[PDB]
Every structure is written in structure tokens, then in C-alpha cells.
Image: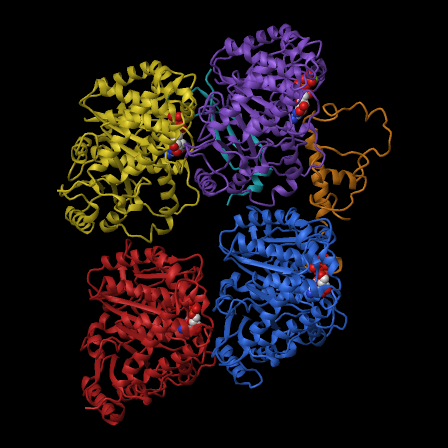
Chain colours: A cyan, B orange, C yellow, D red, E blue, F purple
Amino acid sequence: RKDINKMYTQDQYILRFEGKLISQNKEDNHRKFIISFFCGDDTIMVYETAD
Amino acid sequence: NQAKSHIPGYAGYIPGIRSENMYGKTYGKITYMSVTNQHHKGPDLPPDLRYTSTVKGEFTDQKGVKKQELLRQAVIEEAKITSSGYGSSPLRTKY
Amino acid sequence: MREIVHIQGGQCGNQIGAKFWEVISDEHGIDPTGTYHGDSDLQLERINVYYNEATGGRYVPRAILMDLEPGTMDSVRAGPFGQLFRPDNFVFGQTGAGNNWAKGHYTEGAELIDSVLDVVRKEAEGCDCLQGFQITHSLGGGTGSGMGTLLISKVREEYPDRIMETFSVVPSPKVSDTVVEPYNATLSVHQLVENADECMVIDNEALYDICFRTLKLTTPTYGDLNHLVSAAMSGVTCCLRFPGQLNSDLRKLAVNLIPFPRLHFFMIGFAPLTSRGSQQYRALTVPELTQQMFDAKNMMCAADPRHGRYLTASALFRGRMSTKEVDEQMLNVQNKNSSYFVEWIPNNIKSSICDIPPKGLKMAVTFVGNSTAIQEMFKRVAEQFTAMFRRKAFLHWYTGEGMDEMEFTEAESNMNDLVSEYQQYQDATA
Amino acid sequence: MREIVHIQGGQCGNQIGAKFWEVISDEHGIDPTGTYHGDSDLQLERINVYYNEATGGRYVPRAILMDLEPGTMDSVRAGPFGQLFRPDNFVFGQTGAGNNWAKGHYTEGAELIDSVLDVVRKEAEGCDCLQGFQITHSLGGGTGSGMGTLLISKVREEYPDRIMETFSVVPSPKVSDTVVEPYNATLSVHQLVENADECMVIDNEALYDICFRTLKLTTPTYGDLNHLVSAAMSGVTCCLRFPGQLNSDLRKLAVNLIPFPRLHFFMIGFAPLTSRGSQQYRALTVPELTQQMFDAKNMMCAADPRHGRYLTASALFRGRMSTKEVDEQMLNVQNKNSSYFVEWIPNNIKSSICDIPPKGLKMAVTFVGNSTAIQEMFKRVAEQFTAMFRRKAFLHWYTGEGMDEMEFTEAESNMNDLVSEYQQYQDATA
Amino acid sequence: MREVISIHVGQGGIQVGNACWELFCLEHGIQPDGQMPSDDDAFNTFFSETGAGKHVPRAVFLDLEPTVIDEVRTGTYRQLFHPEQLISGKEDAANNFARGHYTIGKEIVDLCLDRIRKLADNCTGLQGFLVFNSVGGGTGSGLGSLLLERLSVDYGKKSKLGFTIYPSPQVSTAVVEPYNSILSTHSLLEHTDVAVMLDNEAIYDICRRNLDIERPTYTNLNRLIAQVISSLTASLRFDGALNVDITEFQTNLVPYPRIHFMLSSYAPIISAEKAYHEQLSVAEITNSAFEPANMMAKCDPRHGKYMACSMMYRGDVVPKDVNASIATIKTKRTIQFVDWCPTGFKVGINYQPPTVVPGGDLAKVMRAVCMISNSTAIAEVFSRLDHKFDLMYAKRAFVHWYVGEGMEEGEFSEAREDLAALEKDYEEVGIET
Amino acid sequence: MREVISIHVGQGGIQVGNACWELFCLEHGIQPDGQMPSDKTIGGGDDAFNTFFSETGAGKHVPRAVFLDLEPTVIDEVRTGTYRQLFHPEQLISGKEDAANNFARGHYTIGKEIVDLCLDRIRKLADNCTGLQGFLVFNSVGGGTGSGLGSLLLERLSVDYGKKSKLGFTIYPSPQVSTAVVEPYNSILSTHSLLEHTDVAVMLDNEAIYDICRRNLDIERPTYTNLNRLIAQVISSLTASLRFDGALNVDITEFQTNLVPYPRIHFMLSSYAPIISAEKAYHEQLSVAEITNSAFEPANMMAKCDPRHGKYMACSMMYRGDVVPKDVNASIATIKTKRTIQFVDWCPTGFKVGINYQPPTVVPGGDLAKVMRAVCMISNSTAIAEVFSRLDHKFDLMYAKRAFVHWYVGEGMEEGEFSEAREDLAALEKDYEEVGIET
Ligand SMILES: Nc1nc2c(ncn2[C@@H]2O[C@H](COP(=O)(O)OP(=O)(O)OP(=O)(O)O)[C@@H](O)[C@H]2O)c(=O)[nH]1
Ligand SMILES: Nc1nc2c(ncn2[C@@H]2O[C@H](COP(=O)(O)OP(=O)(O)OP(=O)(O)O)[C@@H](O)[C@H]2O)c(=O)[nH]1
Ligand SMILES: Nc1nc2c(ncn2[C@@H]2O[C@H](COP(=O)(O)OP(=O)(O)O)[C@@H](O)[C@H]2O)c(=O)[nH]1
Ligand SMILES: Nc1nc2c(ncn2[C@@H]2O[C@H](COP(=O)(O)OP(=O)(O)O)[C@@H](O)[C@H]2O)c(=O)[nH]1
Ligand SMILES: [Mg+2]
């Protein structure tokens, strides 16, 4: 079963965040990412912007 | 109280359905617009309603349609919910 | 030592490699940032087979990704373990072939293949001791069916002594997502039969059928199909990366499975596979493994293996087990199914055992069977080809870009001759 | 060693097996999770007779459940001890036979039996040393009476040397639940007499009479009937699973109880049977056990055993006892009832002793008697069959699905000949 | 995985469909608005899941008179039924079987067949079709004949069972109803697998004698019929010790293909004022069920021989009591079975007790019985209807109303000789060897 | 990095371009002012809007499409409307005098003075883009200016760019309904012109969509706007594969390699499913099998043509939502097993199915509801010949007595240009019947 009511009622709601990674590697300690959360079905996605 | 608006395949009479247009919408909306009176009546037009032609009377705006549609849905459902209880329905006396 | 490189092209090749590398990464215990976090010492002794060492202690696959459109590679960059690929290997076009073999093989593919050939040559020269190449494609797409086979030809022209493996997804009419499937399939097979040292066909109809009846899962997906294909892919090369009682490299398989140089088309199978409901219910034993192995329904192809006779068979077991039981079970099966085995070549079954089982499973089995039952797919593909070719349908695109109908006639004649000579040995008697 | 598999079909057979396997699990100390929890060492020495090993140390009943409708199996799966069965052994149709022998034997059953035959062949090949097969079914249902007997014929065609046991529930004229019972009962008996090595008849009317008179319980139920049938079944094969003074396998019973190959229809009984309010006062002794095993009302068949002469009798005792007492009691019973025993074959009583009694009881007895009194059931069945068939009523149903009236005529003639030749030996004198 | 499709045509058909579906929705617990009140595939017997929330009954309504359809779609079940499966035409046949068989029904039967295809494509284990129709009415009769003859060639071997309401011997609303009743019987004789008697005066007597309502209505009739239907169908969606399927009616109860008219009784029928003061024993409820006055068909079982009866027992009944009651029934001398039938009783057992409807008359009972029988005594209704039709056809009254609507003059005749042949078939079957 | 350029001509063309353009903005989140919202200030990723837009560097997005008309009323309305800030001011090319249903006026008299600026604006687009996938053209054929300008644009573009792909969404006159009286003439002339100049043409007849609306949408008095919304949804679903991630992608160049077997035969017919309004949409599951059955149902067609009267060559179905590939293949198996729908002896496999993950977007004030599964089919079958035959009959009815001919004679067109169009249609009719026979 897929709870269809939740995706009907919460499709337009999307949360966009700005985040920085933390990792052992030092090359990718400064670069930035934009995260997106779609609460229609709890989907988590990451975008990498290149300056 | 009825329900306001009717099932699509409803034969019968829905008052001023032929007099004052209501062209374009689905059918349930027209029935609702007619059952709760939101339209001009009469063979005359005050200045404001006229000169609002299709692409100028509609096919425009933005999220105001969100607001009106949401209010219509809320009012129609709060009108409908006036029925409950573990006694089924009085269709014995409705029939 | 005796390492190989991975080369994938087209959407299907890229997506197949996407989870093949994921399965290999899970087996070898590498993190998505390239940091080793395994538990066993054997996980690092033969890591050079698929991974190159870099400064900082990280590893990179020898994978080369090609396409005439960049969308599929920009998407595989998003999948898990997609940050292991070396960015220079990504080679993409700016136009796309539009499912056209002529576009993907004559004008745009020929011009584009220069850089990818340069990088492939660099990779082949860099490695210590080259064993061969493995190439994965589908015959339902124009850019794949053209560019992949042209690169097969170019690589064969430069490395005649090395071995070549092709992972071919042929279009079957049941899962027909394109109407020009058989033009491209026949044109790709015509070039592939000449150059590919080994080819193994995979059918999406068979994949979905497996998913519904064997695993009994209601919603099969591209991910499940790719996972099954990747497990079957790793089952072949597990023994080259892990120790075993009887090692058998891809060259030994080529020696023992191909009687005649033009008969190198295979269908495979993987065991065990069961639903979550029967995982505790079932028991893992050699008889169960071999009975699920040799079941006609378990084959990775829609072709019925009981409609023909097996020319040869190859088995790769994973896990610690006695060799006597394996030998006696194979002898018992070969005695009980003598009607389905060719008679003029006795003992047409090869056995190989590796002591390292896959992660999460105690015993595993890979079957590769060369049989005459594969003729049905070619017969139906040729029937569709001649039906669509008798009225010259959709040939204006192909004739407007440099190639003519004489090549079509030659391809059809060669494919029909291949089918006839493949079925000739079925009726041969001693 | 010398183990047998279980196969059941139809709703009644499924219900019988649901209690038989529960009784076996309780006797062997097997929990509904398949985990051994017994107390004695002897409970595990010969558990391979009915249980196979799986990974994790769990045990499985190798029973194959078949039906043309899935309702009975989907209901028994949720019952106690229902998780022991492998899901792979469950085979069900989607249409149903509607209590019609034509649908159960010609149209649907012939096509459906392929999978159950495959799994039965797999189970028979898997076991170390096959002893035979046992089937439980009712003759009042069309789908069972067709599919079970067709499977009997198919299994006999493939294993002519193995032994066959059938537990047949025949529709008695007193308690009738289906109007077409005579037709399918005759059709099933006609095929069963040709292939069954042993058949044991069980009557619901006789079970209900036993429940009302001996146990004196207010409301008899299908659960109590299934429990009695399960105890009767376990009494036969107890000696093969447990040590005893004089072991006697099913083959020895077949040798000692069947004088002529076409006379293999038996009626059985179990002792002791006492009410819950009358357990203390009775003393478990060999004289009580024999006076109860030879009681007419203790028989699981409504046929009167004093209306004919016993051709042969067999008794299996459970519990530690002296053999001299058993022999002298058998001699006394045979001497005091010489009028009811055939005279031209002396010493027509066989006795077997097993040292392991049933759980909760100190001594027990299973009796199997081949006598000429069984002719009455066949006579009344044939009378009802000919009364219903003389007006060709209820017949277009069968004739519209491939059969004809000549098969019915042949079945009736064969039944009449069988009855005549069964009663011929009753009047034979030396 | 099992499904069945119900069709209701005519005013009587739609009114009995409402009564059956209210009982069905109550017993399955689904809300009148269609949403699950919240809490195992049993609802798949009559309903289909939309994926999330409400359910769809597997039923269709057909009528040319939109009054009843409008009433239904304005009632409390407006949200429950699909808007475009309650097909309503324009002009009623007005008791004229020719109007509904040759002029008007053809233009709506295509839409109905399209709807049947759409609903049947969803079902995968379709058991068969149930049809409800008033034969004493023109549009109902004509549409029933058309749908039966179309489905018989569209599907063929698929089972169809019809709960026909034949006219009473003396009490009727119409006067031209003999004509259309005879024509529809002629049509359905070779097109219906099972036909069930639902004459009105018999249930009228039942209600007066047992329910103790001196002034009941058609809705009480419809509720009793709904209880009968729910009983006969509960075996498919409720677990029982001895289950009976739809396919297990034409395999036990139709000795010859032409004899498929079948008459049904039910028990117990008692109001709550005295329902609890009797133990309601299985033996006495069975005796009441076979009692001739407890019949829902105005027929005398004493006047004819019995062929085959099937009882369903719902509740906590025990098979030992079942067989004990059957033995007593066979023992009684007032009921006799035909010579060539040694056993003719088919028993089914279900654990689910009947559900009581609020505002109804029937009380809550832990045991119930429904018996469906084939006996030779049915021929009297056919004989009297034949006399009724002959009295009119002697002087060719009312004939122009049928001639002018597309039928030829002689189409009454073949129906007449079909009834005659069916009669002589009944007497030929009824004689002993 | 992929782009597609849309051109609209005629008032029908402009009001269908506007209709697709609010839908594109809605599904891309574009406000009428060009900012995403004012509330969402991160952005800077998921570049897919470049399929129809181009970034201004900071803020708004501009359309990749052109509006053309010689009647300036519609362009004045558009530049007055709420989208006045969206389109570029100079990209709405408007003339002074309407052709007034005269194809001669629009092809020989007044279209030449405006087609130069049109081509200039086309080049001013093509220079900006780098991965142009192709061109779309929208034009009403029953109008002289639309037909003439479309023919002229196709003729110049076929030599200006050469091999680039063009798709034309034409709306031929109704079989027996007409709003004008001289539309057979200009329709036939335009068909003759575009036959060798368009790569693919698609049928968009009006009475078919009228029947669709009255039967499915239950709207007894629809207006043209609803038809525009349906066409907009169709083309948006068609282009969704190029801007949305899908496990089975299809490109614009993957169209006439799969639906056009001879270069002359390139007329396609489209059907959609499901079409249902909200008050009864949620009542059933809308299974993939039943939506595919409805799509292939003849009465669900957007062209007034009977597929049962003609022989099928090849069909392409495209799904958007959460569809399952094996469910798709099982539906295709049922379609093949069905008898009344037959595929030709020289085409055993004729299915081109594409899959996309993005569900269709619901429009405010529209007729359709929000669904998780949608199918659209584009088909080539021999049933096309009936509309051509009837149009030929109607045109012959007038050319027999030379009615209305002077209105084309006096505007630069010589007398004989009706002929080659007539024999062109006749030759295509024999070509259709020749393709339709089996070997
Ligand atoms: N038992 C029962 N019979 C009914 C009911 N409604 C109508 N009838 C019977 O049907 C007969 C007339 O047919 P109707 O049902 O009224 O109408 P119809 O069947 O749709 O056919 P037309 O008369 O042509 O409209 C009457 O004589 C009644 O006996 C009902 O609700 N219950
Ligand atoms: N479906 C649909 N068809 C339209 C629409 N507008 C116009 N048409 C069709 O267009 C045909 C006539 O052409 P028009 O679009 O009105 O005008 P035109 O093509 O610019 O040519 P002129 O009339 O000379 O200006 C009519 O026969 C209609 O069938 C529309 O909004 N929707
Ligand atoms: N295993 C698997 N096969 C796929 C997937 N997507 C498409 N295919 C198969 O690939 C073939 C089509 O290849 P195509 O995309 O046209 O190749 P391309 O033109 O090189 O991109 C079809 O036969 C599909 O069955 C997937 O996600 N997984
Ligand atoms: N002992 C016993 N007999 C049963 C049970 N259930 C049904 N029966 C008998 O089986 C007969 C009906 O068999 P049926 O269900 O038609 O067999 P099927 O057609 O193979 O499913 C009845 O006469 C019952 O007496 C049970 O649980 N226990
Ligand atoms: Mg205009």
C-alpha cells in the first residue's frame, strides 16, 4: 500500500536547505550543497552547485 | 439541506440552468453556483460585470483560484459532514 | 594481475554498470568516498582486478562511460557509489542518435569515438597484465547498437589476442518498447557475431518473469532487474578475484565452452533465489542448488532450454563444499537428462569451485549454458526483420545517411546462415 | 530409511492431514515452529520417516497439498502447526470442480496435475530409500475423487514396485451431504480398485456412532473425528518408527493381509476408547484390549462384522507387555469365534508388538480386518447409483465434459463383478 | 479473488437492489458514504478497492424511468455508487414488452454492454451474474430478455441466475402483464441457468402471519428478499465448515437443462417481541422451513413431487443436528421425494450469523436456514398463466399494442407451445419408472 | 542543454500557444512575473526549464517561442494580459491587414513583408541555443493567413536549416461542420504545400474533442479554451520526456524513425487517457490496463476517424507517473490478443512505449483532475484516407464550377495551382491504398 492521501495533501510542500558536508577528505571540505526534502512521500535529494 | 451540487449523471431540473449561461466549467461547479446563488440574474448588466471577456474574465490571476477553490471545498465538506452515528441512515423514511 | 577494464555505453550499458560497480563495491567493502573499510584480508589481495590505487589511499574503477547524450551520465552521477567514477572517462555527445543505427555508427559515432578510443588505449596500456575486455549494451537502442559494436570492431582490430565479452540485451517482441528494434538488432548482431569472442543474451521478459514467479514480488523494477544482472555478472568473475579449489579464468571458459569459433552465444542463470517468505523455509544444499540451477524456468532468457539439446555447460560454485558431491550431482543430472544433451561429445559439463561465498549467502551458483535452444530468438527477430523489410518500412532514414539496402540484405543473409548452421549441429549424429 | 511421503488433496483430505500431522508432531515433540522439544532419545532416532531436515535445525513434514480451490489451504495455514508445511508444496486451482468428477478428472485436473506431479517426483527422488506412498481422501467430493485417483494411477505407472496406501472416506447413505455422491463414488472406486495396493474405508456415520456410544460426549465434531482418524493412522506406522519385539512394516502387512491381489479393501479400529467420566475404573489389560478390538461397535465402519466371515485380521499393540499373553488371547478369540472365521486358511490372525506406547496412554491397539462383510457398502452404493442412473438424471453434467454413458456402464459392471467375486470366497469350503 | 456481478432492471429491480445493498453494506461494515470506518479481502466479493478509501459495488442499474434513479442518486448513497453505472434512459415501455424489446431497449443495451465489459475487465475470478427484474413490467421484462440473450453469446458458459417475480394467481397491479410475463418466460427458458420464484402474495402471507404487521409495504418484501440473497451468497465471503459455491448449483440442482425454475423458503421469521422467548432450535426451524405455509411461493408442495433441495445453515449449527433433522424430514410421510432420487438434500454450513438492520422487523438470531428446492408442484402457476393468456388470445385483445411496435402477429404462438412443451416435460418427469 | 523552439500562427495558433504556456509555467513553477516565487531564494539547480526557457542571468525567464498574426487584436490582448511581462515585447509579430481566409493573400501578397522579420527573430533565437532538439509549429488550416504563413515559413526553413526536425500540430476542417465556407480550398493548398515540407503532422479535429468533452468531462457547453487546455496537456506530456528524468526516455528525433515508414506518409493521430473530472475520478483505481484500453478505444480519439475502417501500421504509447513496465507489457499483450485491433502483415511489432516518472500537473479552473498515471498514444494507420477523400470531394464540388476562384486569381495566384494540389492528393490516396495491401 502507498498512502495516497498524504501525497495528495502534501505535494506542494518542499523544504530547501543549504548545507555543508563534513568528511575526512580535505579537498571537499569547502564546497556547498543544496538539499531538498519532499514531504509528499519523504524523499531526500541533494544538489551540488559548482561555482 | 441537500448537499449542494449534484452527481454528474443527474436527470432533473437545476433552476436557472438555461437562462443565465454557466458555460465552461465541469458540471458540479455549475450546479453549485446555481444552488447557492452566485450569478447576476436578469437581462441587464451593470458596468462592472460586462467588458470582462473570457481571456479577460478568466484564464488569468494566479493563486486566488487556490483560495476560492479551497474555500468552496471547505464549505461543501463542512456542509456534508452534518451526518453521523452508528444508526445507518433514515432511508426507511427517505426512500 | 590478469585484470580487465569496464567499458559501458548507452543508457542501458551505463545503468547496468551503475549497479554492477555497486555490487562489486559491496563485495569488496569500499566506502562511497573510496576509503576501504572491509573485514577480511582477502578483500585487498586482488583489488587491483577492478580498482586502481590513487594518492591518499583511495581506489578508482577502470570504467569508461560513453554516450551520445549526457543525461544518462549526469543521472548516474546521482546514484549511490556514483562518486567513484573518474570524471575524464565520461564522454558524451551533444546531439543524440535518436535510436538510429546509422547516426550512432556512421556519422556521429565515428567522429565521437576518437576520444573514447584514446582513453581506452591509455587504460589498456596502463594496466600491468591485460586479460581482456567486457562490454555491456542493449540491442534496442540505436546509439548503443551502433557505437558499441563499432568500438568492439576497433578494439578487436588492435588487440586480436585478447578476449572479449559482450553483455547483450536483445529486444524481444513481448517487451517491445520500440518498433525499430529488429532493424538495429539484426544490424548489431551481424557485426557482433564476427568480432565478439563471447556474447551472452539477457531478456527483460525473462527478468520480469523471474521477478514475478521466483521471487514472488508484486512490483518488479529496473533496480531489481539490474541487481539480478549484476549478481550474474559478478558470479562469472568471482573466481578470478578469490581463491578456490579449481580456478578457471575467462580464457579457460572460452576454451571449454566454444567448440566452433562462430558458436559463442550464451544464456545464463543464477542460484539460489527465493522469496523472503521461503528464505527460512528453504534449506541450502547442493541438490537444491543444482535442481534450481538446471530448471528450465530458471534461465535468464525467455528461450525454452528443453526445446533443444545442450552443446555444453559451465558451473561456478561459491562457498566451501565437497567436490565429490558436486561431481556426483552433475553426473546424476547428465545421466537423468541424456535426451537433452548432445551425444557425440561426452562430458560436456565444466565445474569450478571458489571458497569465498557472496556476502549474505553461504552458497551460490552461476550457470552458463551453450545450447541449440537459442535459435528461437534469432528466428523470431529475423521474421520481424523480413516482415518490416519486405515493404521497405522506415528505411528512408537509413538510406538518407550513407548506407543502403544491400547491407540489409547481407545482414539478413548472414543471420539466416548463422541460424541454419547453429541448428545444423542439433540434428548431427555420430 | 524405509520412509514415506505424504500427499493430500481435497477439503476432507486437508482436514485429515491437519490433525494427522499435529498428532505426529505431538508424538515426536515437535513444536509448531519446527523446533524439536522432545524428552526421550528414541523420539529422534527414526524421525526421518516423516520429517526432513532444514537449515537452522528445523524439521519439515514432506506433505504435498493439492486442491482445485485455495480456500481450504488458506484456512489450514492459519491453524495450529500450519507453519511446518513448505509453501512450495501448496498447489491450488482458481476455478473449482463443483463436486463434479468430470471437472476434477478430465478438464481441470489433467492440466493442473503437472506441478504436483513434478513436486511429488522431486520428493520421491530426494529421499534415501523410498518405502511407498500414502494418500488420504474422501469419495464424496468430485475434485478429490478425480484428482486423487488420477494421481494414484500416474504414481503407479512410474513406481510399480513401491507400495500404495489409501484412506478413503465413502459417502454413507445415512449421513448424506451431496446429491451426486453415488456417481463420483462409483467412478472413484472403479479406478481405485485397479491401482491401490491397500485401501482402508472410513465412514462418518460409524465415527459418529462411536462418538455417541463409546465416548458418550454430547456434541461430536469434525475435530474429534479427525483426531480418531489420525490416531488410527499413527497406530499403523508407529511400529516402523519405534523399536518393538516383532517389527512388521507395511510391506509385511501387505504380504500377510492380502490373499488375492484384487482383495485389498480393509476396515480398521482403535483401542482403548473410554469416556472422560470413566477412565479410572477400567483397568488396562490385554483381555480388555482384545474384547474391545473385537467389538462390533468399535469398528470405524457401519458394516456389521458378524454378518460375514473374517478372511484375515491384524493387530498392532503399543506398550510393554508379555507376548505369551497376547498369543494365548489371540488363540482364545479365534477359538471362541470359529463360526466367524474362514476355515480353509488356518491361523489368519497376525500380531505385532511395539514397546513405545502413545503419549498419555500405557497401552494401545490398532486393528485392521479383511472380512467379507464389506460387501454391504458396495451393494448399497451400487443400488443408489443404478436407481439414480436408470432415469439418466444428473447425467448431462458429466456427458458435456468429454465422458459418455459407456464408462458409467463399465464402472457399474466392474463394481458388480468385484462384489460377486468378493462374496464368492465367503461360501467357499474346503 | 472471487467476484460476482449484479444487475437490477426496472422499478422492482432497482428497489430490491437498494434493499440488498443496504444489507450488504451493513454486514460488511462499510459506511453509507463509502469510506471504511477503519479498524481481509472478503469485501472483494461484492466491492472493489479504489486504492485508498472508498469502495465500488459491482452492480449496475438499468431503467427507462429516471424517477427511481434520481431518487437513488439523491439519497444517502449518492457518494457510494459510480455516477455512470446507473443507466437511465428516457421513455418507459409502459408495460409494453414490445417497446422494451424492439424499439427503445436497443439504444441503451449498447451502453449497458459497454459498462458490463468495463466492470468485468476489473474482475479476475468472476463467478457469474445475478439479475433482478420485474417480469410483470414492460421495460424490466424487455431489458431482461435483451441482456440475457446478449450475455449468452458474449460469454456463453458463464452462469446467470435470475430472481424473477412472477404475477400472483389473483392479485396483480397490471392487466396486460400475462402477455409480457409469458413472452419473458419464453425468452428466459433457454437463456437462464437458474430462475427463482418471488411471487408477492406468499411473502404477504408470511409477513402477516409471522412479522405481525397488518400494514406492511414493498420495502419489507425487498428486505426479506435481501436477507435471502445475503444468506445464499454468504458462503463465498465467509468461512464455513461446508462451503457451497455459485458453480455448485447447476452441478447439484438442475437434473435436466429445461427444468431450472426453483422455489425458496426461509426461516426463522419472527419479531424481537417474542424472538428471544424460544430457544430457536435447529429441528423446529427446519420443520418451519419445509412447512408449506412458510413458503415464499404461492405453491402447494403437497400437490407435487420433490426432486432436489439445498439448505444453507448459518450460525452455530452442528452437522449432527443437521443429519438428525434431515432424518426426521425423510421420516415424515407428508413429504415424498421422486423415485429416481434416493438422496436429494444438499447442505451447506456457514459460521456467520445474519446481521440485523436497525429499523427493521427481523430480530437478531444465532441460527438461520434458507432452502432452495426443485419440485414438480410448480406447474400450477404455468397452467394458470396459460389459461389467463388463452382467455385473452381467444379474441385477440390488446394485440394491436404489440403489433404496432415492431413484433409480428404470431410471436405469441411459439411462446404458447413452448409453455405447453415445458408443461408436458414437467408431467413426464413427474411420473415414476 | 537541449532546446525546442515553438512557432504559433493564426489566432487559433496564438490562443493554443498561450494555453500551453500557462501550463508550462505552472509545471515549471514559473510565476507570471518571471520570478520563481519571491519566497524561494535558493534555486540555482535542476536545470530543465531550459527546454522551453533561457536564463536572463538574474531573475526572470523568457519564452523560447514566437507568436505571429496579421490580425493584431489577439496580440494586443496578449500584450495587455497578465502575462505581458513574460514575453519579449518584439517577439509578438503582428501585421496590419488580415488575409481574411484567403490563402493567396497570405502566401503571395502580404505574408512576404512579415516573413522576413519572422525569420530574423528565428535566427535571433537559433544563435542563442546550442542543443536545439527541433521545431514545433501550430497553425489553423481553415484560415488563409495561418495556412499561408505556415506554408511560407516551412518552405523557407526547409532550406534555411535543412535537415532539422519539425512537427506540425494541424487542425483540419471538420468532416461536415465548418465555421467558414471556403476552407476546403486553402486547406487543400496548404496540405499540398506542407506535404513535402513537414517531417510529422498531427491531426487535431474539433468534433472528436467535443465528443470527448461531452462524454468524459460531462461538460454540455464547452468553449474553445477547454480544447486548448487538452491540446496543451497533450503536448506538455509529449515534451515531458525531454525535461523530466525517466527510466525509458524518448527524444523528438525518436519520432519519425518509429512512426513514419515512408517519407511521404507522415500524418499521425493521437488519443489520450484517462479523461475524467474530480467528482468521480477518485472513485476507481484507474488501472494501467484499463487506461490503455480506453486510450485504444476508438471513441476516445481526438480525430474524427475510425481506426476500425483502416489498417494499423505503428503506434507509440507514452506513460507518465508510477507505471510498471511489465504491467505495460501485459497490457500490450492483451491489446495484441484482442481481435478487432490488428497490426499489418509487414509490421509484427508496432509498439513504441516511453515511460516518465513525473505525474501530470493539475491546472486551476480546468476540467481534468490530478492523477498518478496517464497514457497518450500517437498512431499511424491507413484509416487516414477517409478525411482526405471527403475533403477532395468537397473541393471538387467547387472546382467543378469554378466558384470563388477569382478571389485567388486576383491575388497573384495563377489558375492552375489547384491542379497540382488535386493530383497530389490523388497520388497520396493511391499511395495509401498501395501501402495498405498485404504481400
Ligand atoms: N416484490 C416486488 N415487486 C415489485 C416491486 N416493484 C414493482 N413490482 C412488481 O412489478 C410489477 C410492474 O412492473 P414494475 O416493476 O412496476 O415496472 P417495470 O418492471 O420497470 O416495467 P414497466 O412497468 O414497463 O415500467 C408490479 O405488478 C409489481 O408486482 C417491488 O419493489 N417489489
Ligand atoms: N480547436 C480550435 N480550433 C480553432 C480555434 N480557433 C480557430 N480554430 C479553427 O480555425 C479555423 C479558421 O482559422 P482561424 O484560426 O479562425 O483564423 P486564421 O487561421 O488565422 O485565418 P484568418 O481567419 O484569415 O485570420 C476554424 O475553422 C476553426 O476550426 C481554437 O481556438 N480552437
Ligand atoms: N535492466 C534494465 N534494462 C533496461 C532499463 N531501461 C531500459 N532497458 C532496456 O534497454 C532497451 C532499450 O535501450 P535504449 O534506451 O534504447 O538504449 P540507448 O539508445 O543506447 O539509450 C530495452 O530493451 C529495455 O528493455 C533498465 O532500467 N534496466
Ligand atoms: N472427518 C471429516 N470429514 C469431513 C470434513 N469436512 C468434510 N468432510 C466430509 O466430506 C464430505 C464432502 O466432501 P467435499 O468437501 O465435497 O470434498 P472435496 O470436493 O474434495 O472438497 C462430506 O460428506 C463430509 O462428511 C472434516 O473436517 N472431517
Ligand atoms: Mg483570423
Measured as percent of width and height from the top left, residue D114 is found at: 32, 56
Q: Residue at x 25, y 72 (%)?
A: D197
- Residue C408 or residue E16, whichever sits in front: C408
- Residue E291 or residue C376, whichever sits in front: C376
> Residue D337, relative to residue D255: is it above or below?
below
Residue C378 visible in the displayed image: yes
> Residue F281, relative to residue F180: is it above or below?
below
Q: Quadrant of ligand 5?
A: top right
Left or right of residue D173, residue D55 in this image: left
For residue F309, which quarter of the picture? Answer: top right
Measured as percent of width and height from the top left, residue C389 is found at: 38, 27
Measured as percent of width and height from the top left, residue D67 is found at: 39, 61
For residue C4, which quarter of the picture? Answer: top left
Which quarter of the rendered picture does the C terminus of chain F lie within? top left
> Residue D323, relative to residue B10: is it above or below?
below
Total labels: the figure holds 0
Left or right of residue F335, residue E209 in this image: right
> Residue D216, relative to residue E193: is it above or below?
below
Residue D268 visible in the displayed image: no
Q: Residue at x 64, y 5 (%)?
A: F113
Measured as percent of width and height from the top left, residue E24 is found at: 61, 59
For residue D360, which quarter of the picture? Answer: bottom left
- Residue E93 or residue F202, whichever sits in front: E93
